[PDB]
Structures are given as C-alpha cells and as structure tokens.
Amino acid sequence: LTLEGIQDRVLYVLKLYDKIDPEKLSVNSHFMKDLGLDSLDQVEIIMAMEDEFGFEIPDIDAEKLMCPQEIVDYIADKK
Amino acid sequence: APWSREAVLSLYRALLRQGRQLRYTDRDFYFASIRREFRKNQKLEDAEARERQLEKGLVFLNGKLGRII
Amino acid sequence: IDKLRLFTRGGSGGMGYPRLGGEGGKGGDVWVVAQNRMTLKQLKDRYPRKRFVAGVGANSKISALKGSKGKDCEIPVPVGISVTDENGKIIGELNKENDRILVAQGGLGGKLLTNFLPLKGQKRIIHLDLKLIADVGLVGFPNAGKSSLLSCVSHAKPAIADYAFTTLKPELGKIMYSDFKQISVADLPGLIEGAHMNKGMGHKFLKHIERTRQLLFVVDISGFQLSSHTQYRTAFETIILLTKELELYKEELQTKPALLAVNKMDLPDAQDKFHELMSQLQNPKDFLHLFEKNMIPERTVEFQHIIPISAVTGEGIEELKNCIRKSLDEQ
Amino acid sequence: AIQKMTRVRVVDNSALGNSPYHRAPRCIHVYKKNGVGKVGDQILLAIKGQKKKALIVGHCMPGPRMTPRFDSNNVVLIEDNGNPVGTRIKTPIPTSLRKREGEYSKVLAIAQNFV
Amino acid sequence: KFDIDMMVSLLRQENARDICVIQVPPEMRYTDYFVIVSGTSTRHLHAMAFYVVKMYKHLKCKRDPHVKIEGKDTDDWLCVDFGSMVIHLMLPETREIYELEKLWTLRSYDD
C-alpha cells in the first residue's frame, strides 16, 4: 500500500472526527497540546484511526503516538 | 487517582473491542454510554473512589453480572 | 346543504368515596375550529349521529386517592364554520380556516361524606352555519358554464365535498387567489347547471340551494348573439332579472357582501370589455342607472362588487377574484 | 397479613422512604377484597406525612409451605402513574412475587437481588 | 418462532430509536434476556409495544402464556415480559433516570 495513501486516510479520519476541530491537522498534530485532547480522547482518536486504516494497532504503540506523522509512520511500517 | 493510568487505557481498548464485537444492540449508543461512564466519572475522582470504580470496570470487563446483546 | 344544530358535551366529574381525599374530574370546554379543504378530504361531514360527548372523571379508592380530570370537546367542520349559541346571536363571526371560538363550563366535584357537591357533566347548544355548502351558493342563468369557468380560472382541479346537513352534498370547486393559497366555491347539488337555469337536481335541493346566505349570480358577460346559449336570454335582461330577484329576496343580503359571477369569459378577451361590463354592472344599482342620490328605485344604491370567473387579461382579475373570495369568507 | 395500621419496613431507594421522620411509615388502607393484605397488592403509605400508594413485597407471617419469608413488612413505593418512585431495593425479593397477575415487571428488575 | 433475532428484526422494522439488549445468564432466575426500548413518544412507544406484542402473539407460541402490556397506565414507564425474556419500554431519559442497563449489568455495584 502507498504510504501517502496511509497519510491521506489518517488525515481523513482525523477530519472525520466530530470532537476534533480541523484547525492544525498537521503531521506533528499533538493530542493534548495541538488539539487539547485527554487520554480518553486520545484513545477515541486511536480507535477512530484503527476503525478505517487499522484494526491491527497494538495498545502499547498507540498509547504514545501523539502526532499524525508518528501514526502515519507506524501505519507504513506495520503494512 | 486510579489504580493505574495505562490500565484505564487498556480497559478502554477492551471496551472498544467489545463494542466492535456487538451483535444486536446499538454499538454506537454503547460507545457513547461507555464514554459517558468514563468522561463524566474519570475527571476529578478521588483515589478510593477511583479504586472502587476500577474494580467495577474490571468486573464489567469480566462481565460476570450480565452479558450485553 | 343546510345549517347544523348540535349539543356539545364536555368533561364530567369523578367520584369517591374515600374518607381521605375527595372528588375527581372537572368540566371541559367546547371549542370550534375552522379548517381548510384538507379537513373535507377525510369524509367527516356526513358524520351526523346525534352529536358527540367527552370523557368523565375518575374516583380511585385504593387507598385514599382522588380522581382524574375532565375532557374538552372540539367540533371541526369540513370547509368553514360560523359558530352561534343559544343566545339568539353569534359571538364569533368568521368562516376562514384556523379560527377558534370557545365556550367554557366546568368546575366539578362530588357528593356528600368527605368534600361536597351534586352534579353531572356539562353541555351547550352550538349552531354551525357554513354559509352555504362551502363558502357561497352559485345560482347561474341559462348560459351557465360555471364549472368550466372555475376550471379555467384555477389551476386546482375541483373535488367532491360534503357538509353537515340532512340532505345531499353539493359539489364544490376550487378557485385560485394567486397568493400561495386557494379558496372554494359551491354550486348546485349533483350536476351543476345553475339554479336559475331550470335545474337543481331536486326541488328540496333547489330549496337548499336557495337557502344560501351568500349567493353568486353567474351570467354571460359576452354578447347575447355571441353567448353560448340558444336562445340566449340576453346579458342585460337575464342579469337584471337575476340581480333583481337576489336584491328583492333580502335587502340586507343585497347590502351584505354578496356578488355576481362574471361567466362565459373564455370567448371574451382583454379587449372584449368583459371586465368593463362587470364593473359597470357592479358599481351601479343593478340597472341602467349608475348612481342615485335621493330617488332610487332599489333598496340601496352603490352596491357591492362582482366576482370574476374564467379569468383573462392582466388588469387585476386574479386580485379581484381573491378579494371576492375573501369577502365571501368574511361573511 | 398486612392488616390495618400496619407499620412496614419499606426497602427502596426513594428519598422519602429514606427520610427519617417523627414516626416510621405505616399503612392506612390496602387494595384487598378481604380486609387482609398479602404480598402483591396496593397499600397506603405515610412518607413524611404524605399519603402514597405502594406494593407490599415480602412479609413475615407464614404463607405457603414452600415459599420463603422475611422477618418484617417489606414494601416498594409506586407512583400515581404506578411506576416505581424509588430506584432500587437492597434486600432480595421473592421470585414468586411476580406470579400474582398484575403490575409486576416494573418492580421485577429494579431491586438489587432476588430472594 | 419469536427469538432474539425476531426481537431485533421487530425493533428495526418498528424503527426503535434506542435499543439496549442484554443476554441474561443462568446466574439469576428471572429471564433469559433483558431489553430496553426508548422510542419517539408515549403514543409511539405504546404503538411499538402493541406491534411487538401482536407479532409475538400471532407469530407462534400458542401453548405459551399471554403477556400483557404493563405500564399501560404509566405514560413514561412500561414493560412486557416474554416467555423467556423481558423488555421494558421507557424514555431514554427515563431509562437513564432508571440507569437500568448498567443496573442490570451491576449485580452489586450500584447505590
């Protein structure tokens, strides 16, 4: 699969979230700092990313992503 | 406050797996109810109260007092 | 087509009979609401089975509980309603839809060994007058084409309507007011031909058509030789005869918001002066003479206006028809 | 055997049931054909001086030979609509209590356990 | 027959606004399943209850006992038990004020 397609799917999943405001959906988009998301909100974003481009993400690796670039790199590396 | 912080995330992940494993019930309503049971409870809870709620969540993950459908 | 007289029953009180607590229901009110022709879409105008009643109160006895409340009754009409009571006069005076008139009677209780009074449910004598079958009764002439005239002047197809009467239901036609709304008019029962043109589909039906409070005199606005009748009864002569009969029938009705329908206007054009002839017949005293100051052969000079049918031109014929429909619904 | 003027130890999560007062709650009248109030009927209840209907669930007097019995007069409140005003009953309740034909389901789930 | 799948099909055909089902185990001797139904309005909930009861009756189970619409007097609160299961129809606000599904899921963890 294309890594650019993975990044595009991650961006589409981030923009599809209704709790998140599409203001800074950059590669280093932090949850608690760039978006202001709690640990429950971080887990919700991780589930929402695993819902479309995912369903194989480990809980240990998804607990410390904190950036769309890290999530895109993890998705490219897992696939 | 809680028994552990990463244990709360593990419980949330197991709850998400169970809600994705839902069969007949409104799994979106199940996810919203789980969020309401987590967001409205795990904000500023005290240590003993968070311990009791963690025991309740562990029992719910066990699910011995009922199986959802 | 006739006038209806009904008895309205409201809420009734409850009972007991507990040592603790008390009575039950109360007495509801009688509401009258007028609705559009969509109320006549459901067949509830041939309903009459000696009126309708409302709910009663409750008691409860286990263990010391009081009762329920009463119930109010609303009486709907298919197309328009004029509401009067047993006082010999009407309080509400309208026939347009969404108009409500209420009569209140209640305040109920219960008998004697905890908290006291004797009674039963309440009632009132209501009188519903629809001002003809739908809005007005159309009596034509022996040139009448009122059905085709109404079909040509309105984009809405006419339907079958009914009224709360002891006789047959006359046919009704929809007219367009060019204001995102539509009004209704009524013709002779059964096959519409016009009451003056030797047809009412019955003698009792002719009496029902002639009993209408608001009458519309349809006549040929075209020339007598160009009228769609053989032999035509002349526009001036038949118009004068029908208008004289309508005015002499009641001077108050002549002074009321009654109009004469300008028909056979599908042959006429904008330059045919059909609207000019209608204006000259409406503004005058229904004769050759236009205005009379003191010596007037009629009961009243300068009478009401005329209604347009099979509309043409653009000099406000649709606006005039809408104003005529509004005046007819004003009653 | 909830007869006239019987005091009842109501088991419910209702605040008025939980409300202490000058006296504990006592019934006034019951919905029985005889003058004998058994478990599974509507009875009166004084909550802070307020009349209210309730259902007596679990008694102390000897009933059927195979049935169980508590040591008091346990009851759960009902609304004017008939619904349970309270939330839950801590004491377990007998399973045969629903077998009386009538309003049973609304209390059949709200209590903590089943006796 | 009228199984849990039939109940789900009836809820979907009746367009249940909120459905919450739980499979009751043999730990409690009350039923086999617990259903929570939140509908549009009291008339809508009553109509849904009547449709479900008519379907369960006229479908099958002639030998089974009849089920009455309980909470027919209470506008918000209603229930009907099945031959093996039980449904309760209330508002979602009424369901939350009951907090019944978590209460049905917490045998000893409420107050």
Image (cartoon, helix red, strand yellow):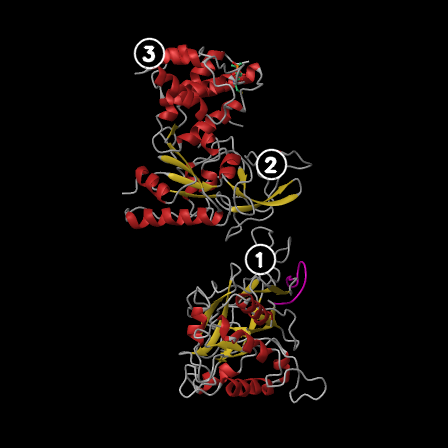
Indicate whether residue D31 is drawn in magenta.
no
Image point 61% across, 35% down: which residue?
Answer: D15
Secondary structure of the residue carrying tag 2 is: helix
Element type where label 3 sits in the image: helix
Q: Residue at x 51, y 47 (%)?
A: E75
Q: Amino acid at mark 2?
A: Gly
Type of residue at label 3? Lys
User: For this rendering, which residue is in front, C240 or C201?
Assistant: C240
* Residue identified by numbered label 3: A78
Q: Residue furthest front?
A: C271
Indicate the chain on which mark 3 is placed. Answer: A
Alpha carbons under labels 3 and 2: distance apart: 60 Å
Do dots 2 and 1 share one subunit? no
- The residue mark sitting in front, 3 or 2, is 3
Q: Amino acid at mark 1?
A: Asn
Front residue of A3/D95: it is A3
Q: Dot 2 corresponds to which residue? A: D17
Residue C121 appears in which quarter of the rendering?
Answer: bottom right
Residue at image mark 1: C59
| Marks 1/3: CA–CA distance | 74 Å
Mark 2 nearby-residue class (10 Å; few <14, some 14–19, many ≥20): many
Q: Chain of mark 2?
A: D
Considering the numbered disc 1 on the image, is that residue within a helix, a strand or a loop? loop
